Amino acid sequence: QMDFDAIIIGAGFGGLYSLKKLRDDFNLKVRAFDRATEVGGTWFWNQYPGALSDSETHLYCYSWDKELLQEMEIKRKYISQPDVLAYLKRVADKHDLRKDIQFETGIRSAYFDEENSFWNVTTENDEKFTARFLITALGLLAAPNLPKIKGIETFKGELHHTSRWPKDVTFSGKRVGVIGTGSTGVQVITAIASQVKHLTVFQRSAQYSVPIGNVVMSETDVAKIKENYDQIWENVWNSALGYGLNESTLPTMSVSAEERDKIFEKAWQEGGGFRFMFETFGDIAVDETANIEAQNFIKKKISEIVKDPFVAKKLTPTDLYACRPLCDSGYYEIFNRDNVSLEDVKANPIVEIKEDCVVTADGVEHKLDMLICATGFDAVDGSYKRIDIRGKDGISIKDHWKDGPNSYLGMMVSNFPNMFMVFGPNGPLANSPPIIETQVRWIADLIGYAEDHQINQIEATKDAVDNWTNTCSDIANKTLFAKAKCRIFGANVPGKKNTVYLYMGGLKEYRNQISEVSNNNYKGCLLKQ
Ligand SMILES: Cc1cc2nc3c(=O)[nH]c(=O)nc-3n(C[C@H](O)[C@H](O)[C@H](O)COP(=O)(O)OP(=O)(O)OC[C@H]3O[C@@H](n4cnc5c(N)ncnc54)[C@H](O)[C@@H]3O)c2cc1C
Ligand SMILES: NC(=O)c1ccc[n+]([C@@H]2O[C@H](COP(=O)([O-])OP(=O)(O)OC[C@H]3O[C@@H](n4cnc5c(N)ncnc54)[C@H](OP(=O)(O)O)[C@@H]3O)[C@@H](O)[C@H]2O)c1
């Protein structure tokens, strides 16, 4: 009666595993869609200079295919964007995935049918499809947050947002400006500084960055990893972050200053943001005195690398909370270069943009041939609201989430039956591929349980969703996060919203949580026959 058992939106990490698991392991008839012309998700769209993974190469991948784990290329310690794209293309090749992906096809609307209990999916070309279940693997790539700057539309030079980075960009002889110093801006600035006539960095808020330590991987090291891949993945599932770290329980202020400086320095040499934050000590994100110790080590490193003390001052975070640092391949070193200028657009904001320059509040005209906007995106739920998703009683996801996202286990939304989110909001804070695998296998097991027991409508209750929001709030309020403003709580509603964007108990406890549900006849889920 319906076109498919399941429809998947997205052909990235999440969508490709959702397709493989439902079609080949559970034998469902499924069609996937993506606006892209190729698989990859964020790794097909984000081809900006310096794009690099946050987790090491041997862990930023799938674990469910052992043959592929052995054949995988481990070139450098972290993996660049074109290599992630080539890997995901290889996954699609090996498992015959593309024949059930409709490319160059965006989904405009998905309407649930409380009669007959399936979903009505319309593409932007007015193609209509029906399916019992809807799998949303949308990521967080929509939509580009561009700087709201007076006159930015009059700029006659090259203007790119890092998410829409065009090929064939050349840098020599050009005066280039970069707005934004987050992870993307740090990666772009570090990669292009040596290639331009002059680089201006327009930073609104300095952030802490630690070295990434991206080194080439020896053939012995690669063989060492593959020989022990089963234990490596077992460590991922029994950890909180899934980054292959020895997650410390050691209190920061329980060692001498000599010892503390040695522990921070060892992680600094090795590289890695989460390593510096969670392999050194166990309370950096929970205790303020511990946090200040981590910051002071990075501030000290900034003041040593950056030789001009006034540029180092400008680069030093004033916030006072190292609530997750970035990673870089030589970011602070860039600012010793004679062709790099740092503009504190907090104490000197960009007021307007003319045809050939960026004007700051001090009147200075910063002449530019190129303006790179590394300015971020919408919130996590932004990708969901940009689709017309109507569930029970015809309520839209825009309205149900007008105050921020909320869900059950990060995978189910009340008033939206038969819809299952992959890497959606209210999920765990950990490495993405292990999270995506955990969710795809749990969702497929639920769909298989429904195909047997002949149930055709699965729905989370308002109580369970609120129980999940409580659990996240209880855990997140134990930490320093929010107070550093990391946009994990985005609430502020008169009757308290406390929409908690992340479950922060770790990947191991997250698998514990959703296992309680699956074991206990899916408590919190409305089953209908
Ligand atoms: C440079 C970079 C490095 C990163 N490194 C790490 C890391 O080391 N560790 C980590 O955990 N995370 C990392 N991330 C985060 C990253 O988003 C996740 O790791 C992962 O790629 C998310 O995969 P996904 O399939 O869930 O979403 P995506 O890769 O974003 O795929 C979403 C796809 O759904 C499509 N789509 C959306 N909406 C619609 C619609 N209405 N119709 C049709 N199609 C649609 C999109 O076009 C997109 O192709 C990194 C991100 C970037 C940009
Ligand atoms: N794993 C990785 O290595 C990696 C790589 C890329 C992205 N990500 C993730 O994907 C998300 C996006 O990363 P992102 O770096 O592109 O965006 P981002 O983290 O949100 O940072 C955006 C930067 O642009 C600045 N900015 C925004 N609007 C501005 C304005 N109007 N004027 C001046 N400055 C402005 C911001 O300054 P303010 O802070 O002052 O607002 C900020 O420094 C992040 O959450 C990140 O975790 C991860």
Image (cartoon, helix red, strand yellow):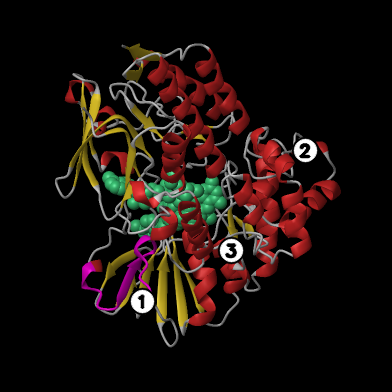
Mark 1 or mark 2, earlier in chain: 2
Distance from the alpha carbon under mark 3 to that under mark 2:
26 Å
Look at the picture and state if 252 lies above or below 308. above
Kindly identify the amino acid type of the residue bearing the numbered disc 2. Answer: Met
Q: In this view of the protein, can residue 314 be seen by the observer?
A: yes
Distance from the alpha carbon under mark 1 to that under mark 3:
27 Å
Q: Looking at the image, which is closer to me, 334 or 57?
A: 57
Mark 1 or mark 3, earlier in chain: 3
Judge: label 1 CB < 8 Å from ligand 2: no
Q: Residue at x 45, y 74 (%)?
A: 200
According to the picture, the residue beneath numbered tag 2 turns out to be 253
What are the residue bounds of the magenta stretch?
153-167
Judge: label 2 CB < 8 Å from ligand 2: no
Q: Which residue is drawn at 49% across and 65% down?
A: 82
Q: Which residue is drawn at 70% across and 38% down?
A: 235
Residue 155 lies left or right of residue 454; in this view the side is left
Residue at disc 2, secondary structure: helix
- Quadrant location, the N terminus: top left
Residue 54 point in image, percent of width and height: 57, 53
Of marks 1 and 2, the one in the foreground: 1
Look at the picture and state if 34 lies above or below 19. below
Mark 3 or mark 2, earlier in chain: 2
Instruction: Determine if the magenta segment contains residue 163.
Output: yes
